[PDB]
Length: 4
Length: 90
Image (tube, rainbow over all chains, first blue to last red; front, side, top):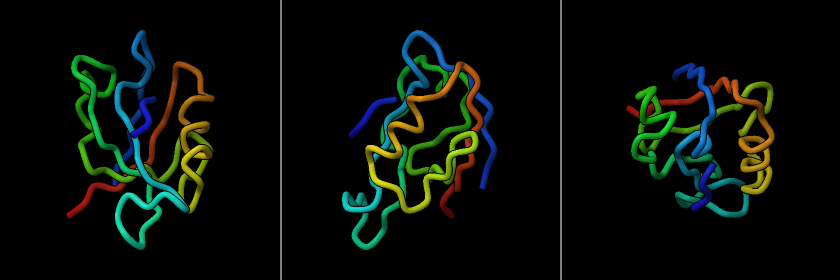
């Protein structure tokens, strides 16, 4: 959902 | 439950999270969850971080009952050295  | 000491690289830390207060990745559960380990990335090279792991904390920043943007901030405002507290499901 959110790449880091 | 685990400790992961990591070095962020060209592609970041190399994985993707979900979840947090108000954006529940599982119903009635605001934990941060690793959803996608990036091929040939820092975590994939390290090998510890597994899919479905729970980020409990990131360096000094605890990711227990935090908003998604709060979590992503914490994982994006960090030097090349990051320690991780995770919880491995059982």
